[PDB]
Image (spheres, rainbow, N blue to C red):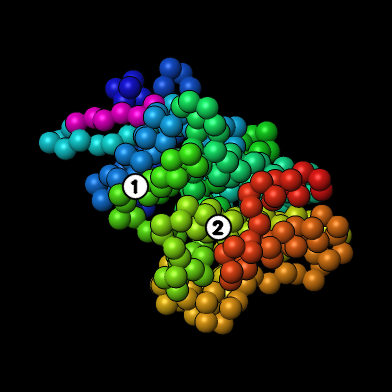
Amino acid sequence: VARDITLLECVGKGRYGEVWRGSWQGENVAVKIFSSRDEKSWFRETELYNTVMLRHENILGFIASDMTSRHSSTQLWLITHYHEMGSLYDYLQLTTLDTVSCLRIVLSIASGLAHLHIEIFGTQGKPAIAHRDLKSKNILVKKNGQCCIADLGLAVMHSQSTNQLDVGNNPRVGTKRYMAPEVLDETIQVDCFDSYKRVDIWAFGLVLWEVARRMVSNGIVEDYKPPFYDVVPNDPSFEDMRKVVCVDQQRPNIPNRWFSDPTLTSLAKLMKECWYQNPSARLTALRIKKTLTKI
Ligand SMILES: COc1cc(-c2cncc3c2CCOc2cc(N4CCNCC4)ccc2-3)cc(OC)c1OC
Ligand SMILES: [N+]
């Protein structure tokens, strides 16, 4: 209930709204107050968390959804577990990673994504879900070293038996920096659920690139950089990414030092298998989880 939560400090702000660190029965919680322009994302997330009952150790822990009316308006709240280490985008800028730390991050993200993509059968079984806005800022680092995926506002679901696709009704567009080439060229088949899984794998390979750069190998480490930092400006436009990803067919550069570390070699091969211009040639989330497990 929103009445029992004490908003203590704002840890994030954007077009989506605000994220607050709050107290609730003597424990820290995360409260997202949605903006009026992003109401459809609150409905979709409430559906995925309350109706679909999405629950996984590598997905942001749902607590409660609520609506509070004040100042002649009604705010839409989402209350989840609070991770004091912040987003993966924040965490990668404060520390370097070793082999275990890197693999724990990338395997946890892969297992959480595979849980979204894999349909659980039986009655009231979880359908296959695509995130469609996967990025380092939508990934949070837990104190055990593992990560969890957040923001289900753009989720899309599908069930194999009925062959029915639920795209929702959200005017929100995904993050342009992480957009797949089929999205930028407007060739993506919006009626096929596999299309939405393949744009997640594409974006997953970009987060994979961000994390691998922070793994120290032979006293060498790369500074943190967002994908395509050296070709697009801040807040890139649609034409900015299309020129890089589609026209020039550019991908993030694999540092040569990665070939001197066996873990980074298998990781560099993994992200390359997520960046195919042909969406059907990209790996599945299950194959990525399997490949990461054998490493
Ligand atoms: C409640 O709904 C959400 C909460 C969080 C969340 C959860 N737990 C911690 C944080 C966040 C938001 C962003 O990251 C943080 C960052 C910081 N700090 C570092 C940078 N600046 C100083 C403060 C502190 C806490 C968090 C995420 C969501 O999706 C991106 C949410 O919606 C689905
Ligand atoms: N952040």
Identity of the residue drawn at 26% across and 30% down: 67
For the residue marked with disc 2, what is the amino acid?
Answer: Arg
- The reply, left or right, for residue 17 in relation to residue 182 is left
**Farthest residue toward the top?**
25
Residue 228, percent from left and from top: 57, 70
Identity of the residue drawn at 58% across and 48% down: 88
Tag 1 secondary structure: loop
- The reply, left or right, for residue 122 in relation to residue 266 is left
Instruction: Please report the bounds of the magenta region as a residue range.
Output: 64-69
Identity of the residue drawn at 49% across and 80% down: 243
Dot 2: within a 10 Å radius of its alpha carbon, few (fewer than 14), some, or many (20 or more) residues? many
- Determine which of the numbered discs, if any, sits on residue 198 in the image: 2
Residue with the mark numbered 1: 168
Q: Which of the two discs, 1 and 2, labels the residue nearer the N terminus?
A: 1
- The reply, left or right, for residue 27 in relation to residue 256 is left
Residue 49, percent from left and from top: 43, 32
- Determine which of the numbered discs, if any, sits on residue 26 in the image: none
Residue 14, percent from left and from top: 36, 52
Quadrant of the rendered image containing residue 188: bottom left
